[PDB]
Length: 36
Length: 48
Ligand SMILES: *[C@@H]1O[C@H](CO)[C@@H](O[C@@H]2O[C@H](CO)[C@@H](O)[C@H](O)[C@H]2NC(C)=O)[C@H](O)[C@H]1NC(C)=O
Image (cartoon, rainbow over all chains, first blue to last red; front, side):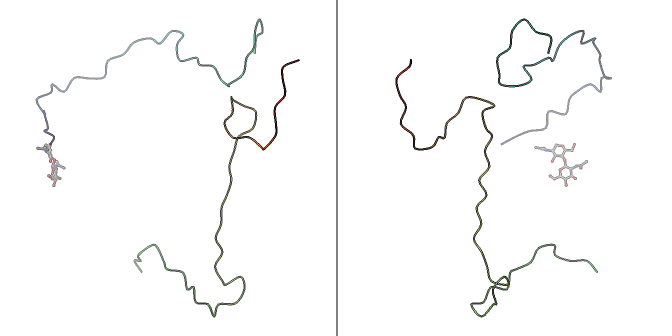
C-alpha cells in the first residue's frame, strides 16, 4: 500500500548558512597535534 | 536500426581455443587502510 498526500503548499527553496560543517575524518588512520 | 541491446554467447564444445568459454573470478581487496577481517594462514605469537 501507498498513497499520494499531494495536499502540499508549493513553498519556495529555503536557505541557511552552513558556517563550518560537513568535515569528516578523511581516512581510517590515527594522527595527533598536526595540521594535515 | 533499433536493437535489443544484449546478446547470447555461441558456446558449442566445437568452439576453438579462445573462442571457447572461461570462468572468471576477480579478487578485490584494500590493504592496511582500516582494521581487517581476512588474513593468511600464519600462527600469531605472544606480545613482547
Ligand atoms: C498520485 O498522483 C500522481 C499524479 O500526481 C499519480 O501519477 C500518475 O500515475 C499513473 C500510473 O498510476 C501514470 O500513468 C501517470 O503518468 C502519473 N501522472 C503523471 C502526471 O505522470 C500517482 O499514480 C498517484 N498515486 C496514488 C497512490 O494515487
